[PDB]
Amino acid sequence: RMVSPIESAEDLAKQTEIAYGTLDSGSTKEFFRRSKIAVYEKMWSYMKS
Amino acid sequence: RMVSPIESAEDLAKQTEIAYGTLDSGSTKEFFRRSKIAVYEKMWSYMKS
Amino acid sequence: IVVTTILESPYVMYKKNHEQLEGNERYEGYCVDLAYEIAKHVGIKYKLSIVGDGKYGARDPETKIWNGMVGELVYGRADIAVAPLTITLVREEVIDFSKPFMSLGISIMIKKPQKSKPGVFSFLDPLAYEIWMCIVF
Amino acid sequence: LVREEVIDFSKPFMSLGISIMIKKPQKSKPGVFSFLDPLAYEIWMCIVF
Amino acid sequence: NLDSKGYGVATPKGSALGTPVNLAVLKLSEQGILDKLKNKWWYDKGECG
Amino acid sequence: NLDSKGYGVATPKGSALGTPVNLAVLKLSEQGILDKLKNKWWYDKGECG
């Protein structure tokens, strides 16, 4: 009864057992590269590394 | 719920099951050697012997 | 301006393709960014250098010669050292230190606690030992 | 920074920061007859009736 | 922590970059840039989450 | 802590006591005298247990 699925980008960033990515050389990749939001910056660092 | 057996230097000093150490030659070892505080004095006594 | 440094993660690191890279673009890490920001604020052109012997700095008790980054600064081989160089009395007597950009200390590392194999008589764990004794009484 | 421009500060003789102070949580002392807590008083009374 | 230490930006004695570097460090500290770098390089790139 | 700050011993700009005071504070820090004084005035005289 306590299980909660992923429901936002913060949930993706916090966890580590689910990988995530995006199309290479696209608009989403540029969005994540240029983002100044903490969660999106963390996501960019993860995907790049 | 997982509880760590150690939560401070005092806990390290009191117990004896868990060993502890430092580098063979470094700033930490010199700090413990020169320490005049009772807790760190006891920790140094344990580590040297 | 020569910025002496020591290769120590995460302070300084080699990029995944540092072989094809030249100059400051080779390196990355906390102190690379710190040197970049300090140069920006002071407005200077700087080149990162890795001290040859890879030592923070100490005085030879026999030759009385400083080594490492402190040696580079003392003898004029470097202009600034952006590295995890602790502020100490001996070093402070031969160089100038800025205020601590990072504060640290001695701390305890322990393996993360992990679920232990159940004991043989772990079925008595829900109730305290005093409860069992008083139940018998 | 503002002060450092007009006076000379030595190295920090004591480090600090911004921290949160909260009223210490009162220790929980179970009542003598707290084993009746799961059910309301009216439930016990109506059970007797 | 069992003691207090700090990392500094060393400079040769009498150099003109001493005061500018000290003030740059203080500025970066007050602007939160040092904390941002610490978080980026310790936790954003951390592999544990 | 939400940030990192430090207390320092101030002096007039260009004063002759600047470097002696700085070295004295560093020596006290390395000798454990500052930690001893803090422990004395915070916990040894601590009304709480």
Image (tube, coloured by chain):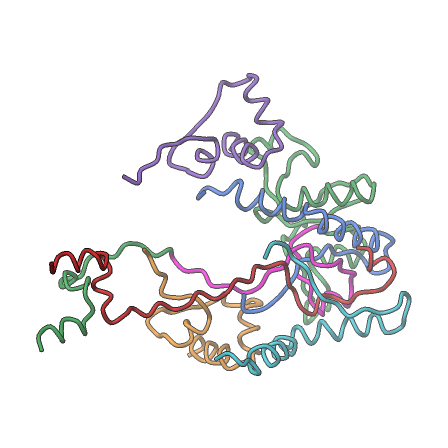
Chain colours: A purple, B orange, C green, D red, E blue, F cyan
Q: Residue furthest top?
A: A26
Query: Measuring 47% from the left and 63% from the top, which residue is drawn there?
Result: C108
Q: Is residue F5 magenta?
A: no
Image: A30 above or below A2: above
Which of these two is toward me, C12 or D15?
D15
Q: Is residue A8 left or right of residue D7?
A: left
Which of these two is toward me, F35 or A10?
A10
The x, y position of residue A32, in whole percent, is 57, 26
The x, y position of residue C115, in whole percent, is 27, 54
Q: Is residue B21 left or right of residue F35?
A: left
Query: Measuring 88% from the left and 68% from the top, which residue is drawn there?
Result: F12
Query: Measuring 65% from the left and 76% from the top, which residue is drawn there?
Result: F34
**Quadrant of the rendered image containing residue D20:** bottom right
How many numbered marks appear?
0
The x, y position of residue B49, in whole percent, is 41, 79
Magenta residues, start to end:
C82-111
**Quadrant of the rendered image containing residue C46:** top right
Image: B38 above or below E28: below
